[PDB]
Image (cartoon, rainbow, N blue to C red; front, side):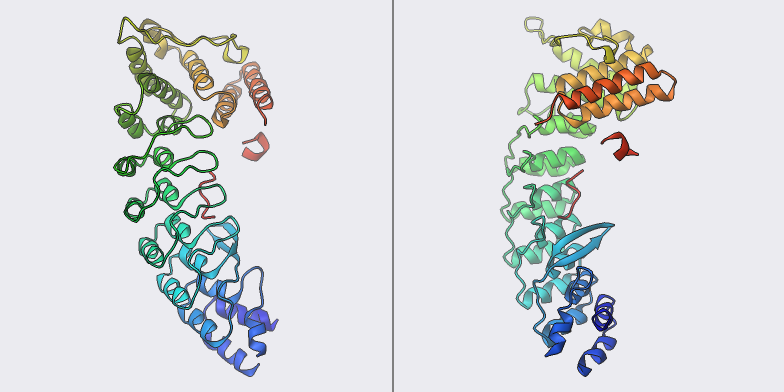
Length: 384
């Protein structure tokens, strides 16, 4: 437990202890290189910003500047992390500066292929982002999901960081492995200002792997500011606008529990559907009536909408019908909200209606293969 001694001295930065322990014992290289619970001494010194510990660990020994291990941020541990990455994630500009000035490689990644740049973008360390970019950081190295620095900056709502990255030449139209673009990240976080900034670079609106445009992503997540903006943008068609407002209404029923707000967006959508008398956009008709939906059908006229507010259970079946039509059975929100609706009926004593909804959610997710009950009793939020 000599290795464990010098390790806690570095981790905690109490330097005078380490200096005395080392100078008594060539072999010191073997000591500081001791990997204690994932972390090297260099890794813990940088992670907790002990500049002079880092400054001396490097200048005294052949201390390995690249050897990554485990580190911890807000409970979520990450692996393979070089010291430059840990300092970047934690925001220790001075540690970041001397690490680089001592020859650390600016683009060496964690296990999940996260760069120092991505880590500083995640936590909003603008000064660190500028220093990394001005010291040759590669803007386009994405993590293992293909999520870029720009995308996480947008997802986190870091406007000045996203702005700087676009000034530096970040590709605004990258897609992740799942088809996510930075426009989707703005939509999901409600970042209207950052979305407008991406449109200054002609960011293209695209469907992701789920078939979601950024307009639909804002509807799924309930960000009405994005939906209002994009339903008045020439790059969205009349039919996309109608479906986006109908889906947003469904989100208002199930996520916001706001039946009045839902009715407002459904009336807008019904108005658009009937605006041109020579080209009515009427509702698609599903193959069958569904028992779990109480055999309901979507309203197909403004007159069918005027009653609805007095009929909360009808509005709730409309919401399920809308989501299955627009999102489809392989989008995770569909079975999720079927199960949530079944749970609310269970809580009020209607177990038959609950069981039918749960059976149908289970049959749906078993029919579409290539948030469980136990689990309950998103992946962008990973610095890695």
